[PDB]
Image (cartoon, rainbow, N blue to C red; front, side, top):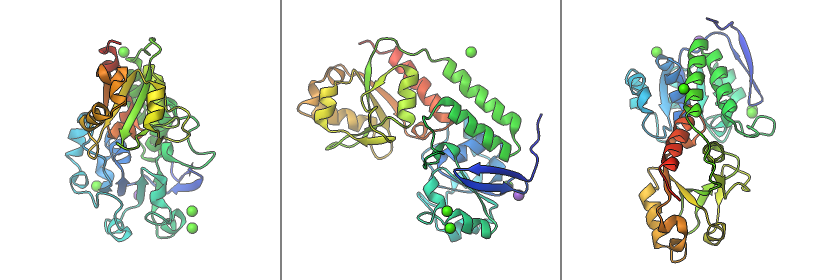
Length: 299
Ligand SMILES: [Ca+2]
Ligand SMILES: [Ca+2]
Ligand SMILES: [Ca+2]
Ligand SMILES: [Ca+2]
Ligand SMILES: [K+]
């Protein structure tokens, strides 16, 4: 039954952010931020959205239906700052840190001067000291709790964390010692899940060894030669609008050497949608989905 005390000061990716009162008019950038506010029962605070990553989670459809901004995003990517400001926001809630730098909408200090708070999803901080190290489920719980505090939504945040933990509790790590390629896009040079993002978190959780684990980033290129030598037991396909799961199956099938891998010959594929690959509460839903598919797979 806690209610937030304002003014509230928080360190958010190394910027001091002070909230004089609960946010009322928020522009959310990326699906992660938009859906987190929907999930916390704060959809009515969303005055604009931009850079959405796909349809909302099915369980957020009824919240999204009450928020006109979800139906009319400002832009497919970053909107102009003028369009953002037209809605008289008190907060810009950015899924990626770059969006509130000079290379994005504007720097955070300049936005503060103009009367606009900024909040970067805590899971998305990129600098040393603030980047998850490593990303864990607790990183994501802490993000929910922090945003809940800012939005005076303490019970809602606790509920959301409890729901994520229940989903995770449904997963028993596979004990077969299997390895996996996490294949995002690319035919000439595959782009794969690296060792420091959601891909690694999810593979660790479901019990797959990531052949891309030595990549020190969320994603990286891996040559066909290196993939073939790694011999992944299972292949996770990210199903995105720009590279479908089927497209990647066809790439694998058509490759004159990778088509001879056991994983490819035996259709040992797991499929995850794009939005849960951005770290957030949906990532746990993605993990459940992959765990269920892996359970159904014989190898
Ligand atoms: Ca409103
Ligand atoms: Ca700055
Ligand atoms: Ca500055
Ligand atoms: Ca249970
Ligand atoms: K306010």
